Length: 157
Length: 158
Ligand SMILES: [Cl-]
Ligand SMILES: [Cl-]
Ligand SMILES: [Zn+2]
Ligand SMILES: [Zn+2]
Ligand SMILES: [Zn+2]
Ligand SMILES: [Zn+2]
Ligand SMILES: [Zn+2]
Ligand SMILES: [Zn+2]
Ligand SMILES: [Zn+2]
Ligand SMILES: [Zn+2]
Image: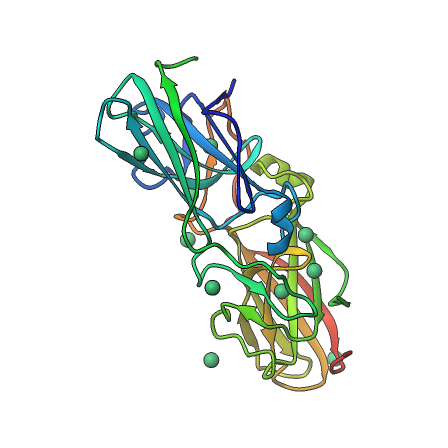
C-alpha cells in the first residue's frame, strides 16, 4: 500500500508524483538517511517525462534519470525546515528518487516541497546538431513540485 | 537520422545491448575528452536496456538502464594498440543512451570493438532489498561485455 503525498504535478518537462509508505531497507544504504528501523517512512518522487518531454529527447512516460532531487519539509506552525536529499534507486516497481525519512518535528500538517535540478553539466549531455539532436535545453533553476497540506499522522501500516 | 550497425545486438546478463555508429555529432556540454564534431571520425552509441533477467533488479523490461559506466575498447586487427574510450550518458532525438564521438586511430580496416559495462558506482544507486517492496536480484560485480570481433571501419557513410 502506497499513500499519496498529494496530486501529481506537471512542471516543465516533468510529470512528478509523490508517495510515502513504510520505511524500506536499501543497499547500499544511501547518504545519511535513517535505517529501516530508525525511519518513520519511505518517501518517493516518481518523475517521468511529459509531452514537453519530447523536446529534450525523452519518450513520454520515460523515467528521467540523473536528476538531483531534494525535499523540504516544514510543519505548519513551525519555522524549522528539514531538508531530505533523495537518491536514485529501484523498488520492485522500477527506478525512482527516494529516501527513508524521520519527521523531525513529529506529527502534524506539513508543507512538502520537491526541488528538482537538471543533471550536472559533467553528468549528462544532449546531441544539439540539426541532423541528430534535440531542440530543448535543461532548465537552470530547480523545478518545484509542492504540496502544502500533507498530513503526517503516524504509520498507516 | 541514419544509423549504421556495429554488429548483432547482444544479450549479456540482464542487459540487451545494441551498438550503432553514424556521423559525428555536436554535444552540449561537450563530454569529457571526446573529439569535436570536426575532429571525430564518427559517433558511436550503446543502446542498453533491461531484458527479462533485468526484471529481478527492478527494471521494466525493455527500458533504458541508467547510471552504468560504459567504456569501449577498439583494437585494429593485427595491432597491439588498444584505444580506450569512455562513453557518456546523453540524449539524442531517439532518447537516452551511452555514447561518444570517436576517431579510429589506426585508420580504415577491421577492428575488434568491445563495450565493458559496469554497474552503477556504489554511491550512485541503490536497491530496495526488503521483502515487502524490494528486489531479489543484484548488480553484477564483473563488468558485462558486449563485443564484435569484426567491425569494419570503411570510412564515413555520410
Ligand atoms: Cl518549506
Ligand atoms: Cl565502485
Ligand atoms: Zn554493494
Ligand atoms: Zn524507494
Ligand atoms: Zn547548458
Ligand atoms: Zn582532449
Ligand atoms: Zn534503448
Ligand atoms: Zn583480421
Ligand atoms: Zn540510437
Ligand atoms: Zn549519441
